[PDB]
Amino acid sequence: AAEAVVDWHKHDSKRMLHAVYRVGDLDRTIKYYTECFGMKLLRKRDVPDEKYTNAFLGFGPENTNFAVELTYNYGVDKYDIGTGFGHFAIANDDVYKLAENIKSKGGKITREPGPVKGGSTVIAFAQDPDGYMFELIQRADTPEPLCQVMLRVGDLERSIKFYEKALGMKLLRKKDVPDYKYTIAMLGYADEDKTTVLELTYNYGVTEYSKGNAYAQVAIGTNDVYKSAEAVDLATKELGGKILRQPGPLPGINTKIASFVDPDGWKVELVDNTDFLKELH
Ligand SMILES: [Co+2]
Image (cartoon, rainbow, N blue to C red):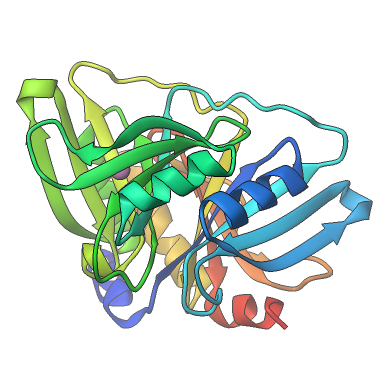
């Protein structure tokens, strides 16, 4: 029934939904992302009983696009990013202009726009109010500007196989750069230049990174949380990682979810696609 998993991922229609992370000041981050990054505010949810507020931002509606799910915990001003979390990436057809705009609005450019060290893709880096890094990548034809979540991992081949077997992702691109002592793999559900990828980074001889308390998880839509969580459970037995929240409906809001950690301890939430669409209304 391991071949049943292979078959399940074929029939399922999985989608990267949002990255969930915590911010010290909700209005400050909304302002930064709308003014500096050109994002839209898509949805907001205050949950006073649990002392938190969500805001969802991105470049198009949540039913078609990947988003950021900001989490503001009442009173909590500051979080620790840790060494594992890499960056989010924003594709834009004119990165020089974008970086200049960011600076004009009072944002922080940490790496000026220009071709990569040996290459000709124009990139830049910005840093947000809480310290999260945003790669800006110049790309002419982008249907999804919110285009990467980069996370650091201890064993690239283990991770690739985990995301393949647990989550049905495709290895889209793999790039070893022995010169600079790193390897990257782009994983996802559609061509890299049309989708949000998970970019996993291995640094030669580094097996351990801290998870911090700032980045929370990535959420992935699925047509069946039970079948997807079975694929996960099978994958975790072979590769490491663990189910945390068993599949089933959330109380009150009713959305069916499961959650788990991968072999490096990065958290993923599976979300029933239809329940998710219903949350948008
Ligand atoms: Co990147």
